[PDB]
Amino acid sequence: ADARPTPAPSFSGVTVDGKPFSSASLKGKAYIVNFFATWCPPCRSEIPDMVQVQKTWASRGFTFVGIAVNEQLPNVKNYMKTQGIIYPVMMATPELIRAFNGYIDGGITGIPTSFVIDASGNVSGVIVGPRSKADFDRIVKMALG
Image (cartoon, rainbow, N blue to C red; front, side, top):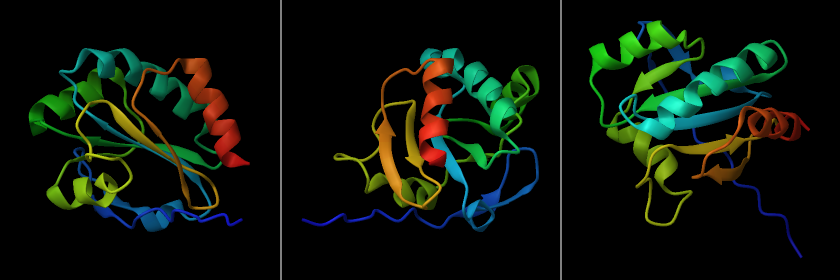
């Protein structure tokens, strides 16, 4: 029997707040890539918990990365300001969507949909249901090893 890893994709770009982002920066780090929209109520419920979890783990080898789908730049930039989003967030591009589409049957068709990449660099799981603050905290602990 074999353990087939699922290497995370490479991706990069410019964030909504005008900063550089490269997945190269994430070598050896666990991270969760969150496809979201700020108008979507389950996203509005979960992103503040994500921001709190980011604060706990930012210097402990983990980060969220947000990719905003079905969105507009001024709306996402203002949500970042109002909610104090402190992890990288990019507007979706077709390339960013196709980078992750392959990990879920049907592709990404609901939001929020998030992908858990462990500190090994493998995609370990897909989140397509709500998660509590405490659930994200435990997921990060597990993903880090």
